[PDB]
Image (cartoon, rainbow, N blue to C red; front, side):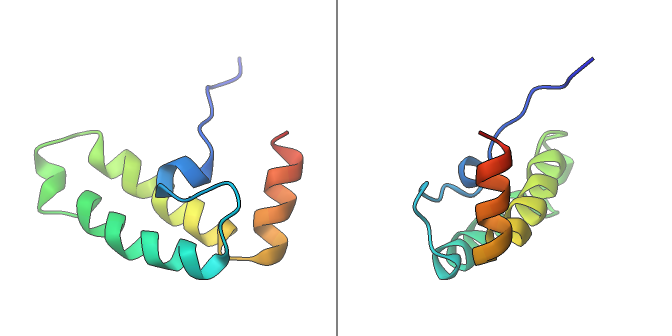
Length: 73
């Protein structure tokens, strides 16, 4: 049983051709959206925030962004 996947780019609202500085910028912007006190009024917001760290953190590298882009193909 394989679960459905969304890409880290999409999570972050960042382009396919994003540079890791771009990713740093979205991460702030979004992290606010999905942090508590919001998180009370959406059970989805905490799930979304959980992507945002995982998504950022990978895409925040030249290496890691690229390896995941290659391996998610």
